[PDB]
Image (cartoon, rainbow, N blue to C red):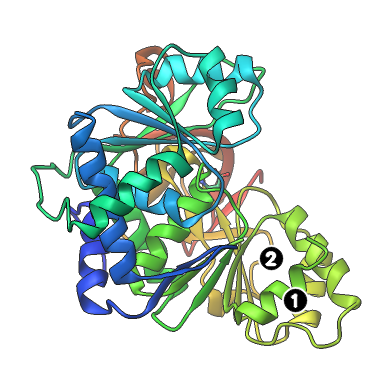
Amino acid sequence: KDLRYGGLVHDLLADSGKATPNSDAMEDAFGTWTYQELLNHSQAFSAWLDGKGVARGERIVVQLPNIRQTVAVFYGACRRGVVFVPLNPGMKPFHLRSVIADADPRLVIAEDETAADRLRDVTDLPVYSIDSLWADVERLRDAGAGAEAVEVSPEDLAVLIYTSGSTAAPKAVACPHQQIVFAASSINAVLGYHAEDIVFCRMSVSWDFGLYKVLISTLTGAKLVLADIALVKSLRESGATMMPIVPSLASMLTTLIRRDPEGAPTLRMFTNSAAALPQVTIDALRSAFPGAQVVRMYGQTECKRISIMPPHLEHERPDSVGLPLPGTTIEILTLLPPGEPGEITVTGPHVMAGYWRAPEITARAYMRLHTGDYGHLDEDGFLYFGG
Ligand SMILES: N[C@@H](CC(=O)O)C(=O)O
């Protein structure tokens, strides 16, 4: 439909960089880049990787907060077939050691010098602080470096997304370009982001919730705001129109909102996944923001997302997590008939390439993804947990 098959991640950027070069693409606490600027810095970073001899198919581990540079690192890596491995700042050191070793990167990018030092205890690989490596990036940007393309297959890995906690064996979903682009386009065919949206994203890009707000904004030409008591003010002052939520973040917002009758009237949508949104929270969001749709979704990192409740149906089938992503199938398992509880299984161009270097774990979950969640479809195709 508007669904993208066979796509490359960095092509999203190249398109918007040319289509709307002067529109605002990324804002963080420190400034704003237009799409041109984002394209230019991503190109520069690609030349920095070339300069360092990081090759197609290799990994970089990047442990950075939500700042513009991280998005440039992401796209610059994609443009060279290099695999982006985003990790959350604040991980415990033994946890980093485990994950870095598993990811097996060519180098590691840290948030600053203190952090670069802590990383150096836990790996022998080369470690660069973003401030220092960025001085080079800016030189390269100024010299116009990195503008050339290089061969990248839609089947090449773009990202590894670690889902394992610190008490678990390291485990990342292995994400090829095609699947990412497709999933972004399929999500967007339901949610309807567009070029005058301002997306307020409080989720780290180390989680696919944030990464896909980078991608969906880039896809549509929207503006992404990379973002505590101040939350309501941030929202209203950014002019935020779209906000991905998780239930704890929604409760906080409804608590905070009673203390501010100016609200944030620009908000038109909240999109919830990761956990079940309780009715009381939904009601409070609608009351504080009657202009906004509250949209239930369900997913796993293994295929990015599984179901979305169409926005226009937000008041119906209160127990459902919605319909399959467009271009994908859900079935319940031996195919069970409607109403019959079984394992939720998923088929489509969003199902990712398995877990990185873990044939054994991959084998049990994976061309059909077995989620280990249980539920049923009703007659219409809507998905429910349990019975
Ligand atoms: N990846 C899921 C959420 C999750 O796995 O926590 C989604 O974006 O719907």
132 or 227: which is nearer to us?
132
CB under 8 Å between callouts 1 and 2? no
Q: What element carries label 1?
A: helix
Q: Position of residue 209 (x, y in %)?
A: 52, 51
Residue 78 percent across, percent down from the top left? 26, 45
Q: Residues within 10 Å of mark 2 (few under 14, many from 20)?
A: some
| Relative height, residue 342 to residue 67 (above, below) | above
**Residue under the image location 36 percent in, 23 percent down:** 356
Give coordinates of residue 196: x percent, y percent.
44, 84
Residue ID at (38%, 59%) = 215
Q: Image point 29% across, 34% down: which residue?
A: 367
Residue at (8, 42) in percent of width and height: 151
**Residue 227 appears in view:** yes
Crowding at mark 1 (Cα within 10 Å: few <14, some 14-19, many 20+): some
Amino acid under label 2?
Pro
- Residue 231 placement: quadrant: bottom right
Reply above or below: 56 against 225: above
Of 196 and 39, nearer the camera is 39
Which of pointers 1 and 2 indicates the residue nearer the eye?
1
- Image quadrant holding the N terminus, namely bottom left
Label 1 beta carbon within 8 A of ligand 1 = no
| Side (left or right) of 153 relative to 346 | left
- Residue that badge 2 annotates: 318
Q: Mark 1 points at which residue?
A: 233
278 vs 269, nearest the viewer = 269
Q: Which of marks 1 and 2 is nearer the N terminus?
A: 1
Q: Is mark 2 on a helix, strand or loop?
A: loop
Q: Given the image, on which type of amino acid does mark 1 rest?
A: Lys
Q: Can residue 349 be seen in this view?
A: no
Tally the numbered discs: 2
In front of the other: 116 or 263: 116
**Residues at marks 1 and 2, CA–CA distance in whole angstroms:** 31 Å
